[PDB]
Amino acid sequence: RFPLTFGWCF
Amino acid sequence: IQRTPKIQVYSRHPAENGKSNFLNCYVSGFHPSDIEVDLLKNGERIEKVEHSDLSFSKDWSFYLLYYTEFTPTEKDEYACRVNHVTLSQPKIVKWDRDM
Amino acid sequence: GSHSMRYFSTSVSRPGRGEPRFIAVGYVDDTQFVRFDSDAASQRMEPRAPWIEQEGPEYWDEETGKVKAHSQTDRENLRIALRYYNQSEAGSHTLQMMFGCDVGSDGRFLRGYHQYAYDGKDYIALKEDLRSWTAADMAAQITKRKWEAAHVAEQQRAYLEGTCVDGLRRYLENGKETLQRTDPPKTHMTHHPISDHEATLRCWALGFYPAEITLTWQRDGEDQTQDTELVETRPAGDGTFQKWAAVVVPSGEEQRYTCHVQHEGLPKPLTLRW
Image (cartoon, rainbow over all chains, first blue to last red; front, side, top):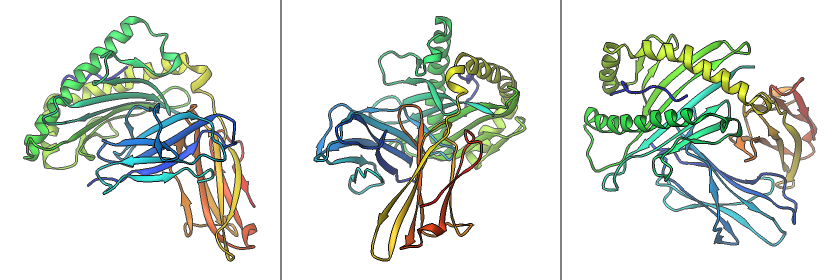
């Protein structure tokens, strides 16, 4: 299962 | 920085003329990821050639496998032709049956 | 032994030629099992190993959703990284991401990962304690402050020790036949003269899995870097791996040289001589 990356803003 | 590909061209099994096999070109340790790899048979480009999905190693560098079904004979000569910014001209590596 | 699950994603910008190319793949150990390509037609997370086809539609729908969204996030990060680095909108950049966990033999969590690279260089990464970040430079420091504010680390820590390891154990079960196999290298030596005073000795390892292997040359029971060549470990294409190592050797001195093969599919390490 691919990670949950919504808040991975730079 | 930019990294020039390490190139290898080899068969899946040990060559024996008349028994079918797979020709591999493996490119690794390179950056950026744009690259063009062709396989040649007596100088001509082979039509149907598969490649793996783009992936990379622990350092950040990219690698790919290109490959094709084939039947080596005594007569035929094979090479991989590799095209990357880091190379002024495409590198052509001849298939060596033992490297 | 241990195992790992990894996801890798790559975004390459191409200005004038539209949207960043995005490609994601996922591995369990050395075996690939999913891929997504922004440029392909399906627009779907796609299976790449036999033992993953058996997942239900709900699984394929969600994995697609996650990975499509991720490609927009990295689309966004590309723009942001241009600004942080004060670079022109003319050129081309790469953003790479890596995520995953390792488990031990008991199936218990060993380690978690989550890191980024921009243009092939370290950007930001989650440290081993999965509590704080390492930022390679001034630009990544900004992102580091943001993710500290947002408590990102703690989300990701909980995912890695939970979902990641649970999915991993579930996959290891679903592909028992295949993923817990441990193929030892089949080995042989080859010999070519280069002149009247020298010859090449090449030591071959074939058909092994997993990729991790060590080949080392000794002269008279001592390691030798000098006059060795050692190629990258390479895929055979049928799921196994290949490697070799070679030394150039004075003629009639072949018998002093020995090649040592190490690999977890091997009871005792192997020794080859010509």
